[PDB]
């Protein structure tokens, strides 16, 4: 179904589709989400139009999987995911990105953490991640530009693709393993709180169509 309410959600099987217009106050416009099918893989789209607050994210419309029981990164064997998506719109300044929070405390709220991992498959416009570039790295056979910074007490690692990766297959464990083995990330003590995929828009008009999305924690 469709809704434009700030915190609308639609649930089906193991997926939740959310409007999550948390930064609406920073600009003028709207955001709506439509959940098409949530049996097996997820199909949904996000629609929006925003002006003002040039460098402020307006929302993170997204799909995510349910994670009733939190587990440490090292305990998880694989975090496979596939994505098929395309953007349409005008003057788009937005990304297409996975977002995952982890914390040492398994009971931490699931909308923040000690760390945030982002994987940007798409990026339109001049925008960039929080923090500064740590150079390029190879993960799962694809090259990414790695960024690092702080959002309050939360450390944020964002891996950005070198082109718009509209058809993707990977394993998010490869990214956690890179941080564990190269940046001192304590995978043995951090629990995965969320596993989400969506878009952060700044300004413009756009529709993110997600034709297919899957993810799991195994
Ligand atoms: C997405 O495509 C546009 C134009 O082809 C480009 O400006 C932008 O950098 C691309 N994003 C990524 C992640 O490479």
Image: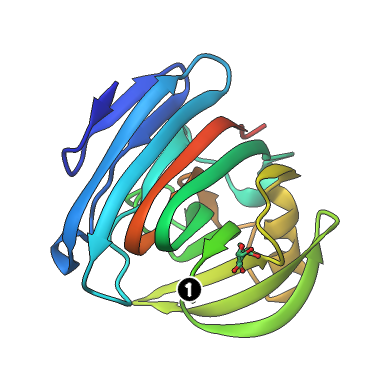
Give x and y (percent) for residue 48: 30, 49
Secondary element type, mark 1:
strand
- Decide if ligand 1 comes within 8 Å of the CB at mark 1: no
* Residue where numbered disc 1 is placed: 155
Snapshot quadrant of residue 168: top right
Give x and y (percent) for residue 70: 49, 40
Q: Residue at x 37, y 25 (%)?
A: 35
Q: Is residue 36 above or below residue 31?
A: above
Q: Residue at x 50, y 52 (%)?
A: 100
In the picture, the quarter occupied by the N terminus is top left
Residue 65 visible (yes or no) = yes
Q: Nearer the viewer, residue 185 or 15?
A: 15
Does 133 sit left or right of 7 as displayed? right
Q: Is residue 23 above or below residue 48?
A: below
Q: Residue at x 29, y 41 (%)?
A: 19
Does 175 sit left or right of 48 as displayed? right
Give the class, few, some or many, for how many residues have Cα within 10 Å of label 1's Cα (few <14, many ≥20).
some
Give x and y (percent) for residue 8: 22, 34
* Ligand 1 image position (quadrant): bottom right
Q: Residue at x 70, y 62 (%)?
A: 163
């Amino acid at each position: 179904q469709t809704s434009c309410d700030q915190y609308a959600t639609f649930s089906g099987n193991g997926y939740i589709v959310s409007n999550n217009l948390w930064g609406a106050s920073a600009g003028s416009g709207f955001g709506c989400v439509t959940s098409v099918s949530l049996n097996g893989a997820a199909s949904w789209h996000a629609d929006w139009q925003w002006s003002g607050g040039q460098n402020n994210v307006k929302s993170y419309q997204n799909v995510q999987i349910n994670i009733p029981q939190k587990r440490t990164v090292n305990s998880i064997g694989s975090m496979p995911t596939t994505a098929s998506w395309s953007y349409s719109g005008s003057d788009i300044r937005a990304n297409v990105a996975y977002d995952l929070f982890t914390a040492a405390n398994p009971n931490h709220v699931t909308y923040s953490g000690d760390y945030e991992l982002m994987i940007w498959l798409g990026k339109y416009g001049d925008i960039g991640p929080i923090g500064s570039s740590q150079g390029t790295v190879n993960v799962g056979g694809q090259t990414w530009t790695l960024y690092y910074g702080y959002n309050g007490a939360m450390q944020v690692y964002s891996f950005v693709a070198q082109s718009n990766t509209t058809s993707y297959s990977g394993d998010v464990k490869n990214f956690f393993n890179y941080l564990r083995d190269n940046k001192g990330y304590n995978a043995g003590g951090q629990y995965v709180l969320s596993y989400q995929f969506g878009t952060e828009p700044f300004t413009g008009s756009g529709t993110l169509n997600v034709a297919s999305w899957t993810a799991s924690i195994n």
